[PDB]
Image (tube, coloured by chain):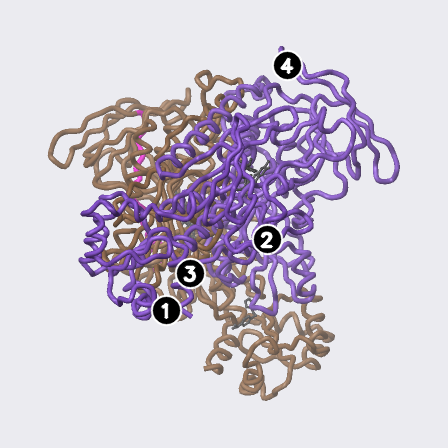
Chain colours: A purple, B brown
């Protein structure tokens, strides 16, 4: 059992030292490597259980049973005297640099998972390249290093969400005694875009500095895997070349889809364009009903826009539908309009974007409702949020042999391995995994440690908590109510729930019975918490701590016996008692 | 062991039905019982693992072994046939109202614990009186039903904290693109107090309605326990009378202390007065360094006041001192002045309070620093926050036999029982317990269930989480870092820590490395999390969820394997890696 772990670690590591904490001969070698500025993995054999068995099994590669032993790319290099002989003869640097390949690791894609995989691999001596290239949108929008979240995703959207929230802050301040007139204050879109884009630019720059200070080679070029170990690159001048790597990580992400209808690509935009748009969108139509669509429609309305959402069927497909409907009712009562059971047919241009004076165009949208009735209205901006997809034909040559699924995502084992033994995939293109930035970052960091440091820890993809940052935020961990009932049967499911009102909302005269939370529990398993759901302010900060308890198997009793922090919204989870089966009202 | 429980349940329960879930004869009794508006506990013997043995032991009381069995105040009443006979003969109401005492329960104190104990007892048929009286402050301040938190504690102070937070919201709004000018906006204290007091008034009313809807007798009179079952009441006309009860719950809380210096009582105020003060305090001296003192100074400063805190020795004695100092430093960087190592000697009056034109007076404060140098300065308002204390001498005739510790608090067993077998104590006066509203509420509700419904669950007072609502909030759960080291030794303690910056602070140009969090772990117990500490916005919402995981025995590995929610502050707890031993900087 242990023998095949050691073969795997020795064959994959770039520079690895087998050591012991107590040994000073090991200390002698560590310092030689530190002074020579050689980075490497170290496996302190006294700090592991089967450590005495590994010391003996090392001899299969080296013919010695003692410590230290140093390896470079699968090859035994020496004990303390032999490495010191290489240092003293200036043979060391050429030994640790000799490789069959240009790089130990090539990462295709410089986003959340790719940059994390890259930086972590370089820590343990892997010679690493990171490739990133941002294909422009149809109107030519492009951005810097860091991926979807940093440039056109979580970071800009939560910053605009905050701008929206500050509007109700201004309203609330009058009731708390501040002398301002909310009625006489307006919002400047381009001022906000300049602040958001300036922060994004400091992140582009930070990532490039991080790569340089880890000796990671960053190539702003489009990557294409033509064979298991060969990557073809194409730079800004359209110059083609080929580099080789031992291990390959695909981390190229996704991009927004367009519907197959006239005018969409020509006259619409997507979220890729929204976050650096130079003019205010004006009267906007959002087509779609995913979290992206609702989040954007949500802050556009809070900033003062005339906003409409076109919903084919339901909101937030895949999420708990009671919570989804409460999310949607809140938005509808605070000035988002909904065109229900409606799909688009064409977009007609009426005015071209006034690019000089910084103004939007004018469009005609024509569609029909699900019964047959017709839709026709004019908008200044149309935003499509109808899903995202990878396009691995751009990245991946079919002859290489990497299996994809029917959606176009990479089929992987539970350690991210593809059907080609040295190629891996992480992040949104890994089939079946939650498409979330913290997931990609963990997957990337954990894989790098297994490749180049002898680690065994895998990424746990179950019960990952989410938050939808609509004007009233919605946090969740675990199963929706309908999924629990389906998997276990309604007679085994108990649901504790309650409305609540933040203390902050009392003096501000906000609504009484709009915030809501519930625990979905399995009776036959000690009333285990199957899913947690909360609609209210700061839902992400509320939910996050409970994801730890859910990972650990929390039960209703665990929540009961824990004491609240007062006054908070979150404490309401510690005294839930009304069940749905009882019929009692959840109001306060 | 099972027989000792049954004898205790039968003796103290007011009205209790022994039953089985599927039992048409039991259902026949239940329908008679609540038709006549008779509240009662019910124990469904088929829901307990040793319900077979319990059913037998009932015969020691009734001479029968079947269900249903109905008891009133320790006396067996009958089976199905017997109870119905009493019903159709109009004898039943007189049976269930038969008592040696006026009340099954007398609660002394109408605050967090007492209201919660009383309402819960009444649900199971206990005849209940709740006594509450508010001794006016030296200047005459008084308030309504609900206790310290509702009237002069958590509720008014967090509303005022929120008023203070809204000032940085208005500042942050400009950077996010709103057109207002923060420097042209001022705060109106009396407008804020009016809104706060109107919300407090609606809580006062809501509690009176809740007691009436539960058939609890509310007496607005001061109570005094003259013998184990005898309570002397004095009403608002000084009429004196005596009521008896079977069980007595003491829940009278504490009040603010005054230092024994000239002018303190005469010319200063406490928090009891601050939350309904008709005029803005103006230039203010806060004397003390507890969380009350720091919280009040904190929002006074955010609302535009000139504020000084006089600190005898250290900030937040009893909390983790590295966190206390970071809390202090932030306040001092945001306009709170500190007079360190200093104590007051006397307050002298320069102007009487102008009650007509609604203005504070003027005071001269004189004191000294620990090295002997002199303090002398003028202030409009002086607020004493130098601790709180009970005064059970005005509650407890010494001859009754209730033992007290050296601080004046009631020594109780771990089921809240005092040295007199039918008297219990809950809330702030229970010696050695955390002094917090959720603790009082939970202790009161669980005690009621044990007295009157046969419950056995005890209140768990370990690892109760806290939040200090200073201008930058500080949430904690478990041991301080210095306590962990003292109990286990520095060599067995490992601390993971990190700075962070809320995403909301980027565009608003706020501080880079002020927010801070750490996890205090025990190496020899599989890196068990001993204490969690976070300084930052929404610290209470952040901390609460983690209290469940700490209750469950969480380890560093459990935090590591849980994925974060992005973008949130709380997610930083899921990727901590820098140790204090390592000497690496916690900046980002
Ligand atoms: C509007 C929006 C909001 C979101 N909000 C959140 C949120 O609040 N929280 C959250 O957890 N997640 C959020 N997400 C999802 C999150 O952004 C993704 O899960 C994450 O970015 C995926 O990381 P990745 O490393 O798999 O891919 P990416 O971050 O997309 O990185 C892939 C990178 O590789 C580049 N690339 C592609 N092909 C090539 C090639 N051939 N050669 C070189 N480079 C290439 C891409 O251009 C891109 O730079 C949001 C997404 C969107 C669209
Ligand atoms: C400024 C301040 C802020 C606080 N903030 C928080 C916070 O954020 N979170 C938190 O958890 N805790 C907070 N606390 C603490 C919280 O208020 C107490 O822990 C809690 O109220 C204790 O409840 P109790 O039932 O023990 O006492 P109380 O709530 O004080 O109730 C006792 C009641 O009995 C009355 N009484 C006294 N003697 C008699 C008598 N002889 N007859 C009749 N009635 C009598 C008293 O007047 C009072 O109304 C704060 C306290 C203060 C002072
Ligand atoms: C002693 N055990 C474990 C027990 C006994 C009775 C009940 C039901 N009566 N009740 C009401 N509120 N809590 C309990 C539940 C548990």
Q: How crowded is mark 2: few (under 14 residues within 10 Å), some or many (20 or more)?
A: few
Instruction: Work out whether residue B1 can be spotted.
Output: yes
Report, in whole angstroms, how far the alpha carbon at label 2 lies from the one at label 4: 69 Å
Q: Which residue sits furthest left?
A: B372
Q: Mark 4 lies on which chain?
A: A
Does residue B222 belong to the magenta stretch?
A: no
- Quickly name the residue at label 3: A8
Which of the numbered marks, if any, corresponds to residue B420? Answer: 1
Confirm if mark 3 falls within 8 A of ligand 1. Answer: no
Q: In which chain is the residue bearing label 1?
A: B
Provide the secondary structure element on which disc 4 rests: loop
Residue B160, position as x, y percentages in the image: 44, 34
Look at the numbered disc 1 and give the secondary structure of its residue. loop
Residues tagged 1 and 4 counted as in contact (Cβ below 8 A): no
User: Residue A416 in the image: x percent, y percent?
Assistant: 53, 54
Among numbered discs 4 and 3, the one appearing first in the sequence? 3
> Looking at the image, which residue is at 71% across and 79% down?
B25
Furthest toward the right, the residue is A372
Residue density around tag 4, few if under 14, some if 14–19, many if 20 or more, within 10 Å: few
Crowding at label 3, few (<14), some or many (≥20) Cα neighbours within 10 Å?
some
Relative vertical location of residue B32 with respect to residue A478 in this rendering, above or below:
below
Query: Which residue in the structure is indicated by mark 4?
Result: A355
Identify the residue under disc 2. B212
Please report, as a chain letter, where disc 2 is located: B
Who's the residue at 32% across and 70% down the image? Answer: A53
């Amino acid at each position: 059992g242990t023998s095949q772990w050691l073969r795997k670690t020795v064959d994959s590591a770039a520079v690895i030292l087998f050591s012991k904490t107590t040994c000073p001969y090991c200390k002698k070698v560590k310092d030689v490597l530190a002074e020579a500025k050689i980075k490497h993995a170290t496996i302190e054999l006294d700090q592991l259980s089967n450590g005495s068995a590994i010391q003996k099994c090392l001899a299969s590669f080296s013919k010695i049973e003692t410590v230290p032993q140093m390896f470079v790319r699968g090859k035994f290099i020496g004990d303390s005297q032999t490495v010191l002989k290489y240092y003293s003869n200036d043979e060391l640097a050429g030994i640790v640099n000799e490789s069959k390949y240009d790089y130990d690791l090539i990462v295709i894609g410089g986003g959340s998972g790719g940059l994390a995989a890259g930086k972590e691999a370089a820590k343990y001596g892997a010679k690493t390249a990171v490739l990133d290239y941002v294909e422009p949108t149809p109107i030519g929008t492009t951005w810097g290093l860091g991926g979807t979240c940093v440039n056109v995703g979580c970071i800009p959207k939560k910053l605009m969400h905050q701008a929206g929230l500050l509007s109700h802050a201004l309203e609330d301040a009058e009731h708390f005694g501040w002398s301002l007139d909310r009625s006489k204050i307006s919002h400047n879109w381009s001022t906000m875009v300049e602040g958001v884009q300036s922060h994004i630019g400091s992140l582009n720059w930070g990532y490039k500095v991080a790569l340089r200070d880890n000796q990671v080679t960053y190539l702003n070029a489009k990557g294409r895997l033509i064979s298991p170990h060969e990557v073809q690159i194409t730079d800004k001048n359209q110059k083609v070349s080929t580099i080789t790597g031992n291990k390959i990580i695909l981390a190229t992400g996704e991009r927004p889809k367009y519907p197959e209808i006239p005018g969409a690509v020509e006259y619409g935009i997507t979220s890729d364009d929204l976050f650096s748009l130079p003019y205010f969108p004006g009267k906007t139509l959002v087509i779609g009903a995913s979290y992206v669509a609702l989040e954007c429609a949500g802050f556009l309305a809070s900033l003062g826009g005339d906003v409409t959402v076109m919903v084919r069927s339901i909101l937030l497909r895949g999420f708990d539908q009671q919570m989804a409907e409460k999310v949607g009712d809140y938005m509808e009562n605070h000035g988002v309009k909904f065109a229900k059971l409606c799909v688009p047919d064409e977009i007609k241009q009426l005015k071209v974007v006034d690019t000089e004076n910084n103004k939007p165009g004018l469009l005609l949208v024509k569609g029909h409702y699900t019964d047959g009735k017709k839709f026709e209205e004019e908008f200044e901006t149309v935003i499509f949020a109808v899903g995202r997809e990878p396009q691995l034909s751009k990245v991946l040559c079919e002859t290489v042999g990497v299996k994809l699924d029917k959606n176009g995502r990479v089929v992987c084992t539970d350690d991210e391995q593809t059907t080609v033994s040295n190629v891996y995939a992480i992040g949104d293109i890994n089939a079946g995994k939650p498409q979330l930035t913290p997931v990609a970052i963990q997957a990337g960091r954990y894989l790098a440690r297994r490749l180049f440091a002898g680690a065994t820890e895998l990424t746990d993809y179950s019960n990952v908590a989410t938050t939808v940052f609509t004007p009233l935020e919605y946090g969740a961990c675990g199963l929706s109510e309908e999924d629990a009932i389906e998997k276990y049967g309604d007679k085994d499911i108990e649901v504790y729930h309650s409305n609540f009102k933040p203390l902050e909302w009392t003096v501000a005269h906000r609504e009484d019975n709009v915030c809501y939370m519930k625990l979905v529990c399995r009776k036959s398993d000690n009333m285990r918490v199957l899913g947690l759901h909360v609609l209210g302010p700061n839902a992400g900060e509320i939910t996050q701590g409970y994801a730890v308890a859910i990972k650990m198997g929390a039960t209703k009793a665990d929540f009961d016996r824990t004491i609240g922090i007062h006054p908070t919204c979150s404490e309401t989870f510690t005294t839930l008692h009304v069940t749905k089966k009882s019929g009692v009202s959840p109001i306060v």
